[PDB]
Length: 113
Ligand SMILES: CCCCCCCCCCCCCCCC(=O)O
Image (cartoon, rainbow, N blue to C red; front, side, top):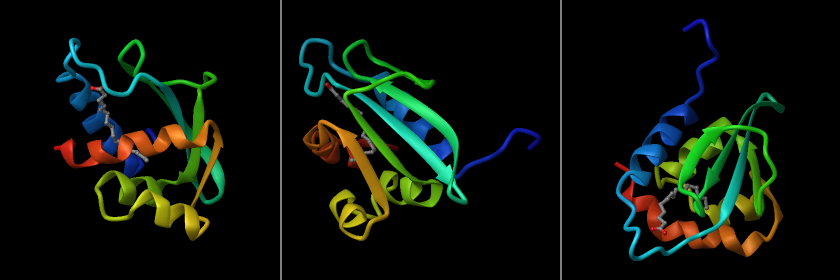
């Protein structure tokens, strides 16, 4: 447990698993998103989910939409307990870039196992 553990790491492992089952013949969301996870206000980890090339990696690259939120918030949204729009209304999540692209991911949350 020497490497910082975050509840949200679990969600990212599930997202990478979900990527394994994409239907190449019927793509639905082809955008690049970045998630900046904070803890105690500081930035602890960055992930880039590239849906154009189909990859999810811990990296600090640029993206079409960037979502910044605390680890607990990412966990809550990713497990389907907190709706994204409510997180935004309560100031628990910040988004830069082409904001509307994030809404395209909502109907896929339920597919995470
Ligand atoms: C609004 C915040 C969403 C955060 C959690 C995202 C979880 C959804 C991840 C789903 C990726 C699967 C996408 C399939 C795309 C496709 O077939 O083209």
